[PDB]
Amino acid sequence: QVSVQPNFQQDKFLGRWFSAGLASNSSFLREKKAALSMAKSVVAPATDGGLNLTSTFLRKNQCETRTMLLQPAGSLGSYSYRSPHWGSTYSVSVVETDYDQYALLYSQGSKGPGEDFRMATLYSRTQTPRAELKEKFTAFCKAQGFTEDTIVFLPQTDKCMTE
Image 1 (cartoon, rainbow, N blue to C red):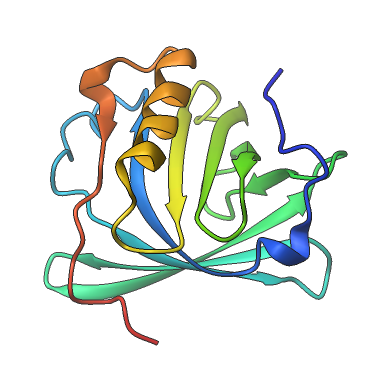
Image 2 (image 1 turned 90 degrees about the vertical axis):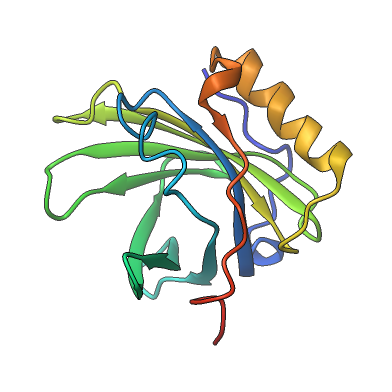
């Protein structure tokens, strides 16, 4: 029931994004706030189909790298993520994007221990999204049922943002 960007163009969605905001129904991403920080995500086509999302971020004094395979899920802009460790599947949709400034992503659990997990993500091409950019995110989050207290604009880190 989640919207995908109309006429989504995957080859315009590639490259470097910064996670500049998030909201979730996690009982303790509600308390990892605010040890949460901005991540650099690099989007690239996977040879087996779909996109690889390579995220780099600061955790407890070091840079950690995570790669997520997003498999096409039936519609342009609609993907699925299968957790290798946790036998959970998530639907991941690019709800709205202008390709060169921002992308609003929505992730929802489908199967497994993460079944009822919900998360909205603000991707930004820059580390410093404009107000009207953050308002689109806030608007999307609140429409989705996220309360103001669960909406977090992730602060920049200096570390782990390099190539």
